[PDB]
Image (cartoon, rainbow over all chains, first blue to last red; front, side, top):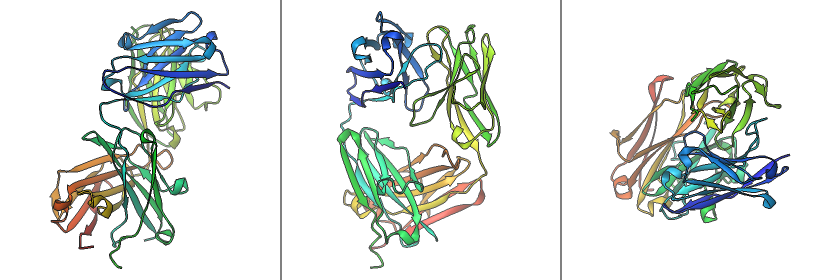
Length: 220
Length: 213
């Protein structure tokens, strides 16, 4: 099978440049063309351009002329996208995809997130949400993940073993920091008799924090 | 160069039903159009190329038609996991994507399950106080949340967030968070979030009292 492996997420200062990579296996890029595509967070797909690795000839959508430079290394079977003079309009996921017309864009890299911001990388505070004493058969608990940058964070419950009853909400950005919340619903007979822990991983800060949801103190 | 005008930008249809998306090119693209499914968290997936050619492994309830400048794409026998954004793409001369069509599945209306949570003792040490209200597994997506403090409606300091439609039960969820300073939080005693949804003229009310513990 064909495999396209892209480089990891990037946090880049406004005005700076960045270079993304895409390494192929299962075919030689010499034999085809390699393409790059943009996806701004809640918007559409935009073709950036392509390269013919055999002769290094490139083509770009006029929108990305100057902004984007595409290259390739034949003996590394890799393709690259360099983006210059970055703005927040360049914040997006960038995909590499294999060329050819029959079929069309069948093979895609996993995407590389580029975040353009002057804000400082900050790990989240993680707060437990235990119910007031008012709370049938089920109980809902939650986790508030506050004051981090950049996106994303990954929130799990009991390391994934609570999966079916979980909702994790999109983050909201305010004063250069994100906040999100996650809920989990479990049978009332199982909490607090059994441990329920929300796990929060923040790739950018290489942090992973656990917070146990402990019942509120009040009834002693 | 070549523009691709994809319509409608959004679709809503019931399980077992059929939808069609139109793509109009600014010039003859000689049947070089392709169609993609894109789910949040995944890369695009090819469904159809050369107007109507099904990519092997894709269910045949996906189909395409057209020629010249006018093309269409259809999904029949709709399933919950068909929730995605779909795109057309011309590849007659370089590449141009259409603007996309976001597909919703229409299930039976369902009322939210509502839960309210006081600020954690941990957060209060920071001097801030977030009251969180979860409104889980409802349909349709339209919903109103009202915060009350001491039974009086509060509109500042509120931030709302909606999930994408769930690929399995076709419901939506949303969180509403009211953030106060700790001193303002501790000046009041009753906190309420009220959910109003077309499933009932009566709001769903969840409250707690702030006491000394």
